[PDB]
Length: 361
Length: 24
Ligand SMILES: Nc1ncnc2c1ncn2[C@@H]1O[C@H](COP(=O)(O)OP(=O)(O)OP(=O)(O)O)[C@@H](O)[C@H]1O
Ligand SMILES: C/C1=C/C(=O)O[C@@H]2C[C@@H](CC[C@H](C)/C=C\CC1)O[C@@](O)([C@@H]1CSC(=O)N1)C2
Ligand SMILES: [Mg+2]
Image (cartoon, rainbow over all chains, first blue to last red; front, top):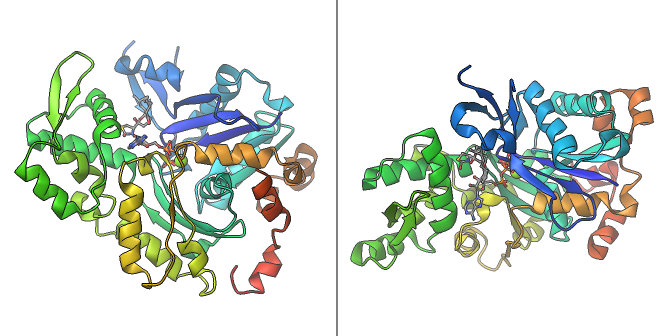
């Protein structure tokens, strides 16, 4: 039975190939005591977060703390899935443009620390494309730590045309803390950030027309919503509901010069071969938790329509389970009979070394 | 599921892709 593990900057999604949903979802963190176990992993750190210093081993989609990542994987196999890794082929995920040395190290750790019988490393955006049933299209994957626009042709990501945006869900939570603080409610601490993440996920949305929506917010209180904190205390949120994810379209809101996600989509397509551009426009797939904002697909449709040739068929696909589409795509892929020839086997690793990840994945 | 498998089975090679200028 094959395993699928999507290693997020924010959340680990893990489970078995062939299942519709990840069996286990837990925070990508390792925590250590602030004052006199030596460490706590994932949900175990979450449950004791108040007394621990938290560290994220994955930054902007790239593994940067290998010792802590090994703890994450150990916890995934033994605590979460309750499996013996030497008994299961394992599919891992990686960010677009993940350095070769990173993927070699991942491969080495899997074969040599966990003794997996076989493994494979797949690109997150590609798995989401597959989950939607396509092998050609352009994927916008906005997660907790990074946002990528990834044009894909017949299963192949087109590296020259990939766009990376270091603006994603965590930055948006931080921005919401800031503007709620300006509103009159102080959100400044580490625990308060989690509260504001929940507010963001509950109440934020993307305006179809930002200027019009701001006008409405100023003219009446119908866009206002109350939010009850865990202790019963209540706050109100007004135009911050849509100003927060507006940052995706206007990165200058947090002082970045970068183009917004609509422009990065357009720029990405325009870097691709002329004959595949219309196929990308017709197959724009959203993925990741930060694409969950109500209104986002219609706003993307609008902005891209304005940028594209006026007769271009534009289509935005935003699947309901797109928080987990990377994992779901991996589940589908690993369970295809036609995929069984793709795995990197232990025998193949032993004779070739970690560099075999370049040839097989 | 059935839909994805076919396109994956007919997935052209890294070489055959460079030929059409699509893949570097
Ligand atoms: N309904 C929602 N509305 C807005 N944001 C959401 C919603 N649900 C989840 N998010 C945000 O999505 C983020 C997590 O998504 P995701 O799990 O795709 O990231 P990750 O894969 O762990 O990160 P990455 O891919 O960048 O390394 C969090 O920031 C979370 O707050
Ligand atoms: C509920 C779930 C949300 C998630 O996305 O969580 C991930 C992981 C999490 C790790 C620390 C937190 C205290 C642990 C559990 C939260 C897990 O940090 C995030 O909340 C960060 C901080 S706030 C920001 O929006 N992303 C994202
Ligand atoms: Mg992700």
